[PDB]
Image 1 (tube, rainbow over the protein chains, first blue to last red):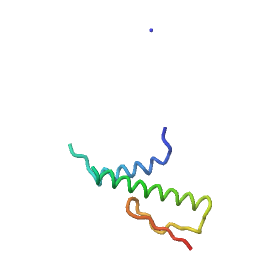
Image 2: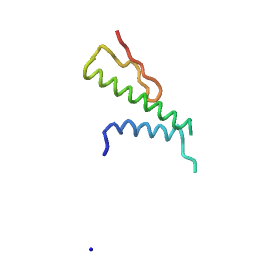
Image 3: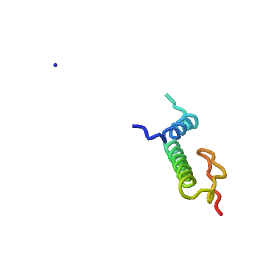
Image 4: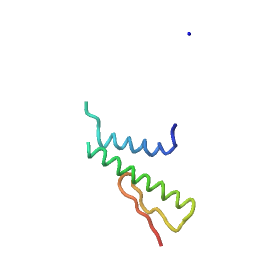
Length: 25
Length: 49
């Protein structure tokens, strides 16, 4: 019939962005 | 929208500059420049001479 392994720092920055700017439904 | 994407981009630029300074300290400079303070997303402070 990838991930360049500098993404730990970008991810921590994403968490800081989540806290500094929260989502709002 | 501007506040969120400007704050994220500026702290991204600070992270890039910190990674560059660690590259310079490891590879070529080495104790000719030292990181004094680094608060992620807040400030970076280097020491020369």
